[PDB]
Amino acid sequence: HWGYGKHNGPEHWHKDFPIAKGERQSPVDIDTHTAKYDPSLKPLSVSYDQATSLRILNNGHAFNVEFDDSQDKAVLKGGPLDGTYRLIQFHFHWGSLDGQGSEHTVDKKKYAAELHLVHWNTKYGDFGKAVQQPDGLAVLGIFLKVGSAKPGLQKVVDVLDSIKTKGKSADFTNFDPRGLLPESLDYWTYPGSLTTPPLLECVTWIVLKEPISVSSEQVLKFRKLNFNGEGEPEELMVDNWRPAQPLKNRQIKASFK
Image 1 (spheres, rainbow, N blue to C red):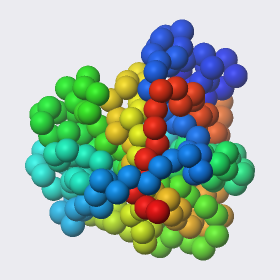
Image 2: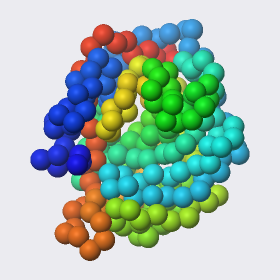
Image 3: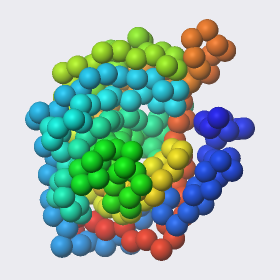
């Protein structure tokens, strides 16, 4: 099945998922000089005060922090969006070394990691229905650089030892995703896709300009995770990023001058 190796990685995905060669694939390189300021874009509204995290999962690709999405508890609105989008999960993509790891790039710069907060449009009732719509999902993307520790990340880091291998989960209640956001909510936005199979072209991307800082020790803990299951040959969970895809007939818009 798909993964990140030489034999199953991103250049192979098109054989099982032909939309991989589609018109609105993600990630992309954000050319800061050609993204245009759009004064019609609104500030983003991130309302995570009542978010209810439940569990963390090693799915064999990354780890997912899952939320209770059975009410409007953690919602994204505004920005480029029409209506209300509910938080369902977050996850990261990261590198083997600090010079790579992000999916989006900024003027070809790769960050050490990238966080995706995934939200689905409430007008479609559930996530599985939402991913079938061109405006079904809104993903908030946040870059990670290595420097000072991010205190709000440490609870995640702490728990990773308990989910080392594919298929392991653990209770992860009471985690506050607000502690993962940068100070500014300035963003770029464009229409794209999920960055893992099935690669569905259902996402409004909102990529924050300001990276968060995490420490080398935090990132190093991500790189101790395993893509394999218990008792199988160890293959470190690193380099679980899809490279930038062709922009095609798309515009990237900036919320800021």
